[PDB]
Image (cartoon, rainbow, N blue to C red; front, side):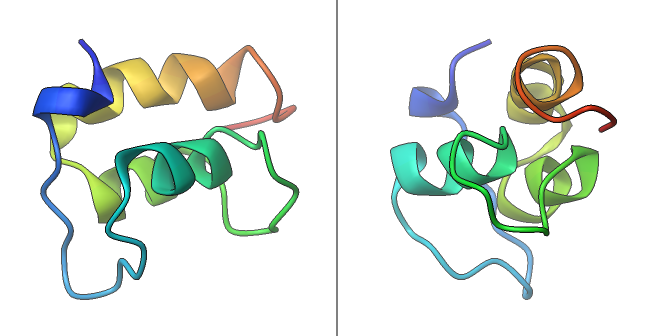
Length: 63
């Protein structure tokens, strides 16, 4: 999926930009909160499934 048509931030997200939230989630920007959790917290599961690949096996060693 793409993060464009998918936002659903639970009450622990902060950023309300698709790009910045995604970037940090996907370890693009070193931040020590990334992995599947950061996807889950800023995005529903569907958005998450994409963002997970971009943390899992793109930048972060472990999601």
